[PDB]
Image (tube, rainbow, N blue to C red):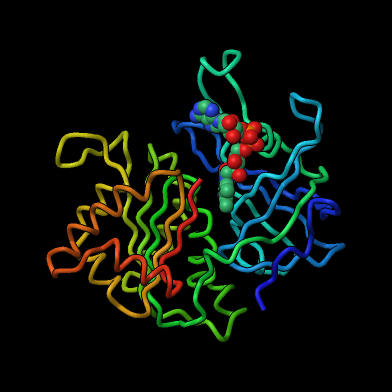
Length: 295
Ligand SMILES: Cc1cc2nc3c(=O)[nH]c(=O)nc-3n(C[C@H](O)[C@H](O)[C@H](O)COP(=O)(O)OP(=O)(O)OC[C@H]3O[C@@H](n4cnc5c(N)ncnc54)[C@H](O)[C@@H]3O)c2cc1C
């Protein structure tokens, strides 16, 4: 039922880039791009929460052909234009420091993708992943804990749930539960998809809450920079009360090691009612209701 591995690295899909638009507005840190690809000519179907591979051209430092890098899909099953013809990605350009051979090193596939022109041919594999799937239940609660490009599967959920054209195209999924996004980025220019996320909250104030953790603009109560863990600590009691519902699913996506502060915050909340969180979390993972994808 769930589409998986319709294309594989030995015979990938050759898709064309349609658009490559900036998501980091002026004044932000780094480059993150929304890249849309053409899927006509082949049979690549996908659903929300899945990933695709991109194989970059040329060779590595050892002369061997470059491997795929996995990217979370930014679009719903229908694509951004709700036509069943496209797929989108949300790609950060990886750039880093001076003690790693050279002066500034740029990541291979992400610099390729972030500078790619419309009309160019791309090797696409997949879709992969059954870890970040949205339930078919319209009455489910969805907590979304996103850091940076961790917004990317959250975009696919929130678009399916709340965009007018998506609701018209999906008669079996008219969402009426509650969704909460806690989004951690460094600046207000770095709030990826800000205007559309804020449009959804103004249109659906009882069904979507939007919380920001903006590190260069806000401080936590200890005087340090505001991160996603601090906003989870601020709302730990509320989030635990929602997690107790049998129909609540929680999604964690973003940088590796973000799980640690979220676990500590929900541990203090769960302990007030005599529950050890690390054990309750194991049962949620078993039930398929605690979904993690960090990198
Ligand atoms: C399931 C999954 C989903 C993902 N989704 C997305 C997504 O939606 N958007 C997105 O932008 N990315 C996503 N990523 C990460 C993405 O796959 C690639 O890892 C990333 O884009 C960098 O690939 P590259 O080819 O640009 O870098 P490479 O050229 O392979 O460079 C990466 C390598 O350089 C080193 N390196 C990286 N950062 C540093 C640092 N700060 N200091 C020192 N060394 C470092 C490491 O050796 C690392 O293996 C996802 C990863 C996974 C596993």
